[PDB]
Length: 317
Picture 1 (cartoon, rainbow, N blue to C red):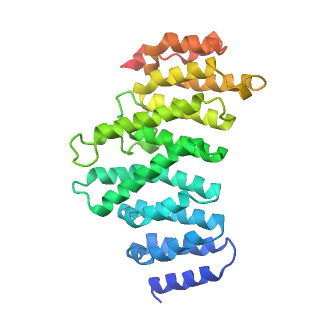
Picture 2: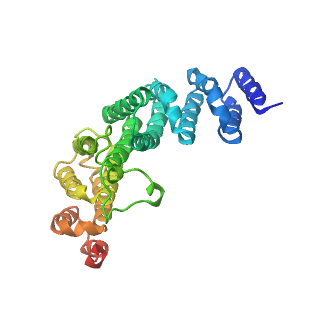
Picture 3: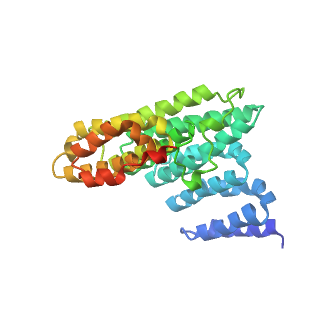
């Protein structure tokens, strides 16, 4: 029997399995159609995507993972799969939503790169980009989800967005895994469709949402520390934002979220200090030395710890 005959037989078996172990069979299918005979991907998309209706949470999560792998293998499948991903982002179960946010964090930057490399934008490709972009806007709105784990994942997606939609600079720290990710500097300024200025504004607006979130008197401990880490990552990857990040830290410290200001205060300060020190260690910090140092002392950072983390101006070259 042929590969596509095997795929049909596995799919028919997966349909008879009544527990999550059907994912074993679906991953066999995914390996056949994504890696063994990639030409089959197109032919059996419908069959895999059909499992987005499965009642099992792990099965819907599998389908989100599958969409990510398929779009990473052929980004144009995003044309037929963005709508299914949008349904999973609105899932009734928060674990499916979280997994869909993870996936958008990966796929947004790849759809954008694809738009940026197209000189002529088809109707399908335009509606696909419109949807990618409303989904990003909806995930930013998820900063106000009533679910703590969703807000946490939204923070990370928003972090990734701010970094995508701002330019790399010469002293930008770039985690090696993100070396080849698109950023604003890699966007031609006369692309007829994707407008540089608009994406910049959009990155700035995303950052303003994340700064406001950070300050909010009602956010939780896990959200706060995720946001603090995100802001620190942003300041080191995009040093043009360092000022705004330092200021956000000053502001959080002046106005502690009432629920975290007594028994939890030691923890919040230790967290704020650890993140602030990571910013200080970045050479662009030398421009804000008095402001950072003053904030570090006010948090009760020992002098030795400030001194140890101060970058040399040699690292400014």
